[PDB]
Structures are given as structure tokens and as C-alpha cells.
Image (cartoon, rainbow, N blue to C red):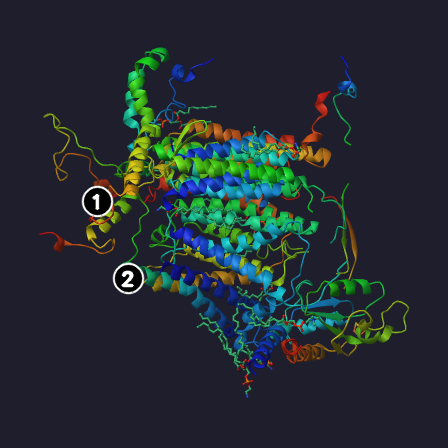
Amino acid sequence: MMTYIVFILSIIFVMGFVGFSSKPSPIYGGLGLIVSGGVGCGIVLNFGGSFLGLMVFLIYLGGMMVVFGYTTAMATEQYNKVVLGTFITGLLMEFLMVYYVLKDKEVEIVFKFNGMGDWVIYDTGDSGFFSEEAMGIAALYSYGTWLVIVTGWSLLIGVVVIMEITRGN
Amino acid sequence: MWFEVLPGIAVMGVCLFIPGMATARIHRFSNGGREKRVAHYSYQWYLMERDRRVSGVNRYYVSKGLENID
Amino acid sequence: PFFDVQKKLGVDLDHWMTIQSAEQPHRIPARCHAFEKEWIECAHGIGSIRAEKECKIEFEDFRECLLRQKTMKRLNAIKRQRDKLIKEGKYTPPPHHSGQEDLRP
Amino acid sequence: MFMINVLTLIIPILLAVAFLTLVERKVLGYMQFRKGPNVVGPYGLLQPIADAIKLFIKEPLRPATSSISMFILAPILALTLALTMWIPLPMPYPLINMNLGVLFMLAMSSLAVYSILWSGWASNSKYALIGALRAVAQTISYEVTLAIILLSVLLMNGSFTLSTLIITQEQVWLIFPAWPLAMMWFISTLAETNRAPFDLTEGESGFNVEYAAGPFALFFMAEYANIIMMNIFTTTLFLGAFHNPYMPELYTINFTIKSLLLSITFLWIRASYPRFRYDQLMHLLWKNFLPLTLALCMWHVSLPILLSSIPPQT
Amino acid sequence: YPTKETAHWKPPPWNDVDPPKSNLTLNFGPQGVLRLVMELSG
Amino acid sequence: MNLMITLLTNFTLATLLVTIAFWLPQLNVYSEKTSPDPMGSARLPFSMKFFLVAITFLLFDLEIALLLPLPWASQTTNLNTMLTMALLLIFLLAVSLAYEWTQKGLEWTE
Amino acid sequence: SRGEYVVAKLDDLINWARRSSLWPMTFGLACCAVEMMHMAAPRYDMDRFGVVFRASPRQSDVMIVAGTLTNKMAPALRKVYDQMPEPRYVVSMGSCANGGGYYHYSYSVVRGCDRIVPVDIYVPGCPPTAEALLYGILQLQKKIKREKRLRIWYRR
Amino acid sequence: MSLVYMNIMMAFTVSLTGLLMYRSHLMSSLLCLEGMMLSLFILATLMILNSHFTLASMMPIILLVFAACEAALGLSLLVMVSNTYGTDYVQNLNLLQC
Amino acid sequence: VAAFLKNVWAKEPVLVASFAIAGLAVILPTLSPYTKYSLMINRATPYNYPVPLRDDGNMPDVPSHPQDPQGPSLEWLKRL
Ligand SMILES: CCCCCCCCCCCCCCCCCC(=O)OC[C@H](COP(=O)([O-])OCC[N+](C)(C)C)OC(=O)CCCCCCCCCCCCCCCCC
Ligand SMILES: CCCCCCCCCCCCCCCCCC(=O)OC[C@H](COP(=O)(O)OCCN)OC(=O)CCCCCCCCCCCCCCCCC
Ligand SMILES: CCCCCCCCCCCCCCCCCC(=O)OC[C@H](COP(=O)(O)OCCN)OC(=O)CCCCCCCCCCCCCCCCC
Ligand SMILES: CCCCCCCCCCCCCCCCCC(=O)OC[C@H](COP(=O)(O)OCCN)OC(=O)CCCCCCCCCCCCCCCCC
Ligand SMILES: CCCCCCCCCCCCCCCCCC(=O)OC[C@H](COP(=O)(O)OCCN)OC(=O)CCCCCCCCCCCCCCCCC
Ligand SMILES: CCCCCCCCCCC1=C(C)C(=O)C(OC)=C(OC)C1=O
Ligand code: SF4
């Protein structure tokens, strides 16, 4: 059961999306996307993506969903059947997926998926005195020159774009 | 006078002294009278799991020296 | 229009992140470095139409390295037959597969 | 045995937050030429106990909430985040020794604005919502200089590991190469915890005025846990103490004295200044701290290269 | 070719500009003692 | 694993204290209260300036996310390129701040 | 009996915690506000009794009506009284809050704040001194000390 | 293939069909769009960490940053819609039928 | 060039300090004699295993043992 733990988190992940995709209200939907971001971060962390998971917290959740909840609280003035039916529909489809891929150890929705716990696909070695993911992100400044240029230019242009379109003149 | 504030500062300072003293004594109790093994990198974890395998008691901290070879 | 500015000017804008077998930081290999190197050295220069039918073996070995579908299918088959024989009682697992063997090194 | 270690972390957190209220009332007393509490206990040592028992049997204020669920979730999130900021703190050994503890703390402190935002929207008062939006905008503004100052300091550390930050400061305090970063860091931590002169939730409504005495006390103790925690983190980060590995209690006494003095420095700053106007601390961030912070970030990138003083990765 | 569905459609404006279809008032009450009525614009 | 235990303990103690703070004074039988704000019933007027400071936070937070691997990137052997791109990213964050200045974006929350 | 002893000790505990942590909301109406400020000033210092200085009205335990209550403000006084969580007490400070005072026969003054809110301590003076107000606050603490909420609850 | 990829693809399709079936709010649409981005982040991350392909570890951060800038732009558009009608309702955005 | 500088140091000392520290961060690594040692220390740090060479017979610069004289040395790092 604990060998399936990432899978279990992924189930909660899918459940969290049926939280906000059914769209109850943008604030409860924001909360559902926050919970989804936390459990997807846990999925990332359990493969060895420590820095990427903390980017999910600091930049996706603590950076961007803060601005989503902030903008949302400045609208939709404070105080359904389609939401509840959509939520139970998505939940029953997800538990039928779980039931099939656990009873058969294999399923095929669009692609063939094994039903074993996802620990089986890992590597059996060590990376020495470094995280490989940390060194691959550190390579953004040594090997990623064009990527840094186009990303920083897009962010500068994005600042210019937001200041042009939010002015009305 | 001003030293009347020192009992509350003393109580709060003891309350801040408790967690580090507690985790140091618990790390020395749980790891054979020594520090907890810091394994930030997979080589350190490899050495630690090798220690757990060569100890024979399924405890990484039980160290085997030159007495374990002939 | 693939205006190949990078080969024209000799610059390297994005070829470095393109494949797993490229120059990596600290010489870290991918898990399918050898399979991808063999598929690329097979399919180099001969074009995609010939590369689909002439380098099928290296590409299938590389895809089966990437997604491990045949390997996990085989592990499914072995574990399922083992669980069936445990249910029938005609098999018993050894001590080294039960955790009673005092591991190697 | 690990659960005992978690309890000996988090129950002394609650006791230190309990008596920090007494220390604040006493120190603010003597700085205001009066005494603090000295009647309720001997030297007022029973004032936090009496106040906790008073607040936990006060009538529930019973608001009409726009959301019941987020009104419940905002104190839970505040207390959970205020307790999880302590677990990577090397004092001298962290509870959870993690490789990226600095970034973990920056992330879990970036998540703390949702309690303010959810409690502001979960109230039906529009003016409480305006105050919540101002408090969130203040906090996310000063998080920018938190992240960039913290990056510029950890360029001398070598990693995001908090325990390595003790090894970094064995020859000298890190306040000596980074006192401008230290002073902008300290004022930015003063503005994170909504602490005076940046307390506009008491400047003339707070975001959590619709809560009863119990839940508002939980917000209050999460705030003081954040205050003690950020002072400990600033102590670890700029005033790193001597550590004998055979005698860990020397480091524990030393960082405890320094963190107490830094928390009393928070108490002594609120006894000294008037508040900022809201645009004035926005001016303080965007037009004063952030240009210096970017300039010193360029300086602390280029400085280990030009002096051959790049710290090790491990 | 106007049909029954597309019969309420009028042609768009000539400059393609549609017509645009307040400020806050606060009561800082008696809660010395002064009542204030604010008209704020941000 | 110890982290998940610690998170569960912190979350459980927080939920327990919130349950006590919401349900220990509910046991009293005090009195029923009829009980019939600076704005009375006027709808919340939108502030463009709070949204602009939140978006400026978001964009500078993305630029910070780019800046975060620098204590690792200083360990490279292509140090001239690394230093050039680090100074270029901090300079582009400074140019973003300067353009946010000069078009009066940092005004009335300066 | 055991239950009477237990509810007596719990009464003593909760009365101790309530009288030792009184939080006031002061209606600074008129000249008595100046003397409440002197009762907060460093000579008398209400904060050493556990009586904080200017708690918010939705967390305060006692409403000190310090000044003249006029007809134009009596619904605001009553609204703040109705917004206070229980147990709430009312200290009437000075002659105009007590009985109308020097403006008793006026067309525009409520003749004592006890026509508007229930009152626990009447503190007389024009103004009463800060020491006299602190006397009234200590008398309010003594009134809280002899409360019998759980003993009456156990006897009902 | 692996079992976690099933759930991350199903999450992307759930956020897709949420983004492809509007109810009333444009903010709920932007949340579904960012759920699509989040599932792309998770899926890219699990592949790149699985494959030990080192240089693409900087790839999901890039996938975050641009798209979050995209999110910022979307929020700004919503606010301009909210500054015309008072609400972000998608049925107000129907003037371009004629 | 001097009255403007005293003017901006009188009006805006935060920004003068900002542009001055940024200018030092830009120009000073190109003028430093120790920028070379940063590169030399980062390439002297052995993250990987020194995979040995097959002795063909003619490699006079490659040692047979770590304690041999030929090979890359780190006397400059111990001395500085
Ligand atoms: C960590 C332990 C403690 C650390 C130290 C902190 C202890 C002291 C705290 C005192 C209480 C503070 C309470 C809050 C104060 C808030 C107000 C305030 O101070 O605002 C900040 C003020 C704001 O100033 P201001 O707003 O008053 O100024 C007017 C500004 N205009 C014109 C735009 C309106 O100052 C700063 O922003 C400076 C921040 C720190 C700068 C450090 C610079 C170091 C030197 C660099 C080099 C200089 C030489 C040039 C280059 C030479 C190269 C060789
Ligand atoms: C890490 C360290 C943390 C430390 C936290 C605590 C700090 C403060 C410590 C306590 C300071 C002294 C407390 C003294 C309490 C008052 C005692 C007293 O005199 O009570 C008198 C009262 C009535 O007495 P009575 O007999 O009626 O008097 C008439 C006599 N002719 O009788 C009564 O009220 C009944 C008796 C009440 C006794 C209460 C005692 C105080 C409770 C403190 C709780 C915490 C204790 C420490 C916990 C951590 C260490 C284990
Ligand atoms: C089975 C029998 C028991 C039944 C359940 C009861 C449990 C134990 C409760 C505490 C003990 C019961 C008695 C409570 C106090 C009664 C006596 C009292 O009130 O004495 C008054 C005395 C001070 O005299 P005072 O009137 O204040 O005079 C002003 C000075 N001129 O006051 C003092 O000297 C100080 C009084 C302190 C009261 C005790 C200490 C506080 C409570 C500690 C335990 C609960 C809280 C734990 C921590 C909570 C979180 C912080
Ligand atoms: C509204 C909902 C309720 C709100 C209140 C409660 C939630 C908010 C407060 C708690 C936040 C939880 C944060 C969990 C992850 C934190 C990041 C993290 O794990 O960092 C620590 C560490 C990374 O460092 P490193 O040393 O590199 O890794 C170990 C390698 N030897 O990595 C590790 O040590 C890895 C340990 C194993 C993996 C842990 C996975 C945790 C479980 C999934 C996420 C749980 C939170 C989901 C909800 C988020 C908020 C909505
Ligand atoms: C080349 C190195 C890298 C440079 C880029 C990186 C810089 C790091 C710091 C980032 C700063 C970001 C924001 C900068 C905005 C500049 C524009 C500006 O602020 O103009 C307005 C200002 C007058 O302010 P005002 O509009 O009235 O605002 C109210 C406050 N009084 O006008 C002014 O105050 C005039 C400001 C310009 C003059 C500053 C002169 C400083 C000179 C220091 C010595 C030379 C250093 C070498 C670099 C060259 C500098 C020109
Ligand atoms: C788990 C509960 C532990 C005890 C509660 C926290 C410690 C006591 C703090 C009391 C307190 C003080 C002194 C206080 O002054 C205050 O007002 C600003 C509060 O907020 C309402 C308080 O909560
Ligand atoms: S009792 Fe006297 S001093 Fe007090 S408020 Fe009335 S008129 Fe003024």
C-alpha cells in the first residue's frame, strides 16, 4: 500500500482537478487547484525533484495562485446541481479507472498503462555528491544562454504588455 | 526596575533552549551515542545503506572496524 | 520554412538540450544513453523514410528502454504466476526473498 | 522516538509564544516609563495563562461568514504553516535535515498569505476584505526582497542547506560581508509579520476581526510563532554561533540568546516609531529596498568570482 | 441575408466604439468621538 | 517519511486547537442575540492599483524563479558565460523595475 | 459533595482568569477620557493589572463609558454594547455618565448611561480621579471574583 | 507504461474538458487553463526525473515561467472585462456576433 | 558630470548607491586578478571519477600512479 503512495497522491491529484474543473465558484476552485498543486508537488518530490517541487510551492502556489485568489477576491461579490453532478461523474470515472487498473494490473484508455506501483521504473544507482536535477537546473546559466535571453526578454515584454493594456489609453 | 522583565525572558529562553537540546539528545540516543548521519546526497545514502548491510543488525550506526576482518 | 540560422551562422542556440546523449553537466548519462546513441548513429543521414524501416530494432530497444513496457509486462506475468502459486500453495518463497539472508556487502 | 522529538519542538513553540506576550507587555511597559504586568502572577508570570483561559471561554463572536469552510481553514493554515517553518531550523541540528531548507522556508512563508486572503474573503465585511488585500499586497511585496536578499546571502553559503550556514560562519559572522543585506532583510522580516512600523491591520480594520476570541488567539499565536521563527532564522543566517559538535548545547545557548535579543529588538522597534502610511512602505519596498537589493544581488554574484571565494557545493 | 434568428442584430458602430454603459463612500461612525463621511476615489 | 509525520502532527495539532477554539465556548448557554461597517451596502469598488502591484509581484516572482539556481550555477566551469547571464537576468529585472517606475506604475502605492 | 467542590474550584479558576484579564473598551466621550488616559499613564498603569489599553470593541470585556452620553450618540453606545461578547460589564465613569451630571436638565443629554445599557460599577466624580477610576476597576474585579455561575448551574 | 502517467494525463484531460466547457466565470476558465499547465509541469517533471535527462531539468521551470506570465496576461484581460461590465461573465463577451 | 553627481547624491542616495554597486559588479570582475582562480578552482573540483587511460606505450605526460610527478597539480591552491 505504501509502495503505491505516489499513485495514491496522483489519485488525489485527479480528484483535486475534478474539484476545480467542475467550477463550483472561482474561490473554491482556487482552493481545489491549491490542494492539487500541493499533491502534485508531493508526486514531484517523491521522484527526487526537490527544487521543482519547491518551485510548485514558491512560484505556482505562493507566487501565482496568490495572484489568482487576489484578483478573484476583487471580483465575484461575497455572499449547484451541475457542479455536483460533474464532480460525482469525474469521481466515478476515476474510481472505475482505479478499479480496472488494480484488478487487471494493466489498462488501456488511450495508451497501455501498467498497474504495478510506479516504484518499479526507477534507477538502482547513485548520483554521487550532487543532485542531477539541481545540476541540470544550474546548467541554465552555463548551457542555457539562448533560453535565458528569450525568457528574460519575454518577462520584460510581459511587464510592458501589462502596463500597456491595463492603462486604457 | 528593568530586571523585572528578566523572569519572562528567562522562561521564554528556556522554552527556546528545549527543542535543540532535545533533538541533540534524541539524535545521540537513536544513533549510538553519535550524531545523526547526514545523507543529503546519494553517495552518502549509499555509504549509509552499506553500513546498515555490513552491521548485520539492520542498524546503520553500529560500526564494524578492523575486528570484522581477519 | 525551417530557416536553419543555427547551422548557417555556426551558433548553438538549442541543439544542446535536444537529445539525451548530448554533452551533459558533470558527464551525467541518461538511463537510455546507449540506446539513444545507437538509434541516432543508425538513423543518421539516411533520411526519415529509410530510417523508419531500417533502424526499427534500435528504435524499439530505445523505446522499450524509455517506457519499459515489455519489462513491466514480464514483471506482471512473473508476479501474477507467483501469486497464483502462493494461493495454490504449490510454491514457497526462498529466505532471500523473504528478508532473512544478511545482505551482500 | 521521533514523535517525542516533534512534540519537544512544537509544545515549547507554544510556550515561548505564550510568554512572548508577557515579555512584550513588560518591555513595552518599561520603555513607556511604566511597568508591565506584575499583579496576576509573581512578576506577572501568570498573565498569559489567565489571558488564555479568558479567551477560551469568551462568547463566540458568531459571524455570518461568506464561506464556512475557508473561515475554518484560515486558522488551520496559519497554525500549520507557523509550526512547519521550524522543522528545518538548525539549532544546532534540525528536526528535519533537508537539503533545501532555505527554499522550503521561503515557500512555506509564501503560502502564509492565503490565511489572510481566505479570512478576509470569508468575512462578510467589505472593509475587512480591503484590509486583507492591503495586507496580502504588503506581504507579497516584501517577499520579493526576502527571496532576493536570501539568494544573495546563500551565494556565500554554497547550497540551500540551513545546516551548512553554520559551517559558512565559523570564522566570522555573515553580517560582516552582508550588513546591508542584513538590515534590509531585518526590515523585510519586520514587514512580513505585519509588525510595527508596518502594522496597518491596527492602523486607522484587521483581516481577522470576525473571528471569535479563540480563533483570533490562534491567529495571534501563529503570528508570534512567525516572529520568533524569523528572528531565529535571521540569527542563523547572519549571526551564526560557535558550534562544538561534542557539546551542542553551547550552540543552543548562543543562538537562543541572539534570537531573544532579536525578538526584543522587534519589541523595541514597536516602542519607538509611528506607522508608515500604506503607500510609504510601498515606496520603501519598490523604490528603495528593491533597487539596492538588485544591485547587491549583482554584487554578491560577481564578488565570489572576482575574489576566488566561491563556496563549495557540498 | 437576414433571417428570424439574425433579425435583432444591428450594424456595429462607425468608430467601432461602444458606449461605456462611481466612488466609494465610507461611514467612519462613532464606534473625542467624531462621525466622518468619506467619499474616497481609491 | 519523518517529514510527512511532522506535517501530519502539525496539521493535526492545528486542527485540534481550531476545533477547541470553535467548540469549547459553544457549550455555554449565554444568550440568543438579535443583532440587527464603513460602507453600508455599496458594492466593493475595484482598485486597479492593487491588481497592478499583485501582477508586478507575479512577474518579479517569475524573474526570481529564474534567479534561484545561482548558488548552484556558480560552481560551473563556464564562469564567464554564467556571470554574464546572471548579471543579464538581474539587469533585466532592474529594467523591468525601471520601466515600472517611469510609466507611473508605482504610484499611490509607490 | 464532590460536584459542588469541583464547580466551586472551576468558578474560582474562571473568575480569576476573567478578573485578571479584563480588556476595556473606553468610550472617550468627554473630559473623563482624559482621566482614563491618566489611569493608563505610567503613574497608575492599568496594564500591570492585566487591564490592557484600548482593546478593540469585539474582544473587550468591559465598556468604560467615560464622558457625557448625548441623545445623538446613545444608539451608537447601545450598538457597541450589543456587539460585545459576553461576559460584558459596564463601568459608568463620572457624573454625566452616571446621572446626566452638569447637563442633566439638558434637552440633548441622556440622564445617565443606565437608561441605555445595564451598568455594573458607578464611578462618581467630575471627573473622578484616575485613582478613583482604578478603584472602580478593582471593585469590578472584586465583583467578578464573587460570581457563582457554575455553582448556580450545578444547583439548577 | 507507468501508472502515474495515466493519472497525470487524465488530470490534463479533466482540466481540458473543464476549460472546454465554460459555465459563467472567466476566472474559472483561467483556473482550468492553469490546471492544464500544472499537469503539464508534473508530467514533464516525472519523465525528465525518470529518464535522468539532466539538461531538461531546467525545462519545466521554463514551462512554468512563460505560462505564468501567460496567466498574468489572462488575469489582466479578465480585469479589463471586469472593468467594462462589473462581472467576468462570459455571456457579456458577445458583442462580436455583429 | 560633477554638479549632476552631487545633485543626485543629495536627492537620491539610495539610487546612487544602487547604480554604483551595480557598476562595480559589472566592471570589477574584468579587472580582478583572482577571477582566473575561480575558474581554476571550479575545474579542480573532482565530481566525477578520473577514468584512466589505456597505456598504449607512448603517453609521457600521463602518470601511472597518483604520487607520480607528471599530471595536473594543485600547489597553487595549497599556496595561493
Ligand atoms: C539583522 C540584525 C539587524 C540589522 C540592522 C538593523 C538594525 C536597525 C533598525 C532600526 C529600526 C528601523 C525601523 C524601520 C525603518 C524604516 C525606514 C528606513 O530606514 O527606510 C530605509 C531608508 C529609506 O530612505 P528614505 O525613504 O528616508 O529616503 C528618501 C528617499 N527618497 C528620496 C526616494 C524619497 O534607506 C534605505 O532604503 C537604505 C537601506 C539600507 C542601505 C544600506 C546601504 C549600505 C551601503 C552601500 C554602499 C554605499 C556607498 C556607495 C558605494 C561605495 C562603493 C565603494
Ligand atoms: C519551561 C518552563 C515553563 C514554566 C511555565 C510557568 C511559569 C510560571 C510558574 C509559576 C509561578 C508561581 C505561581 C504561583 C501561583 C499562585 C499561588 C498562590 O499563592 O495561590 C493562592 C491561591 C489561594 O490560596 P489560599 O490558600 O486561599 O490563600 C489564603 C492563605 N491564608 O491558591 C490557588 O490559587 C490554588 C493553587 C494554584 C497554583 C497554581 C500554580 C501555577 C501554575 C503554573 C503552571 C505551569 C507550571 C510549570 C510547567 C513547566 C514545568 C513542569
Ligand atoms: C479536583 C479539584 C480541582 C478541580 C479543577 C480545578 C483545576 C485547577 C485550577 C486551578 C486551581 C484552582 C483555584 C483557582 C484560583 C482560586 C484562588 C484565587 O483566586 O486566589 C486569588 C489569588 C490572587 O489574589 P487576588 O484576588 O488576585 O488579589 C489581587 C492582589 N491584591 O490568585 C493567585 O494567587 C493566582 C491564582 C492562579 C490560578 C491557578 C493558575 C492558573 C491555572 C493553571 C492550570 C490551567 C491552565 C493551564 C495552562 C493554559 C494555557 C496557558
Ligand atoms: C488547505 C489544505 C490544508 C492546508 C494545511 C496543510 C498544508 C500546508 C502546510 C504543509 C505543507 C506541506 C509541504 C510538503 C512538501 C514540502 C517540500 C519538501 O518535501 O521539502 C523537503 C525535502 C526537500 O529537501 P531534500 O533534502 O532535497 O529532500 C530529501 C532528500 N534527502 O523533501 C523531502 O523531505 C521529501 C519527503 C517526502 C515527500 C513529502 C510529500 C508530502 C506530501 C504531499 C504534499 C502535502 C501537502 C498538500 C497540500 C498543500 C497545501 C494545500
Ligand atoms: C551600469 C551598471 C548597471 C546599471 C543598471 C542596474 C542598476 C541596479 C539598481 C536598479 C534600479 C532600478 C530602478 C532605476 C530607476 C531609475 C529612474 C528613476 O528612478 O528616475 C526617477 C528619479 C527621480 O525620482 P522621482 O521620479 O522623483 O521619484 C520620487 C522620489 N524622489 O531620477 C533619479 O533619481 C535619477 C536616477 C539616475 C541617476 C543615477 C546616478 C547614479 C550614479 C552612480 C555612479 C555611476 C555608477 C555606474 C553606472 C552608471 C550610472 C549612470
Ligand atoms: C494554545 C493556546 C496557547 C495560549 C494562547 C496564546 C498565549 C496567550 C496570548 C494572550 C494574548 C495577549 C497577551 C494579548 O495582548 C492579545 O491582544 C493583542 C491577544 O490577542 C487576542 C492574546 O491572545
Ligand atoms: S463627569 Fe464631568 S469631567 Fe466627567 S465627562 Fe462629565 S462633565 Fe466632563
Circle 2 chain: D
Instruction: Say which mark, if any, is on residue D246.
Output: 2
Q: For the residue marked with disc 1, what is the amino acid?
A: Pro
Q: Specify whether D162 is left or right of A14.
A: left
Foreground mark, 2 or 1, reads: 1
Q: Are marks 2 and 1 in contact (CB under 8 Å)?
A: no
Q: Residue at x 63, y 30 (%)?
A: A164
Instruction: Tell me if residue D235 comes above or below residue G65 in the rendering.
Output: above
Instruction: Say which mark, if any, is on residue D108.
Output: none
Look at the image and tell me whether residue E14 can be seen. Answer: no
Q: Specify whether H35 is left or right of D176.
A: right
Instruction: Tell me if residue I62 comes above or below residue F35 in the rendering.
Output: above
Instruction: Tell me if residue B61 comes above or below residue G101 in the rendering.
Output: above
Classify mark 2: residues with Cα within 10 Å, few (<14), some (14-19) or many (20+): few
The CB of the residue at mark 1 lies under 8 Å from ligand 4: no
Circle 1 chain: C
| Residue at the disc numbered 1 | C94
Q: Nearer the viewer, residue B18 or A89?
A: A89
Dots 2 and 1 on the same chain: no
Q: CA distance from mark 2 to mark 1?
A: 45 Å
Q: Position of residue E35 (x, y in %)?
A: 79, 57
Q: Position of residue G87 (x, y in %)?
A: 68, 70
Name the quadrant of the N terminus of chain A: top left
Q: Position of residue G150 (x, y in %)?
A: 63, 76
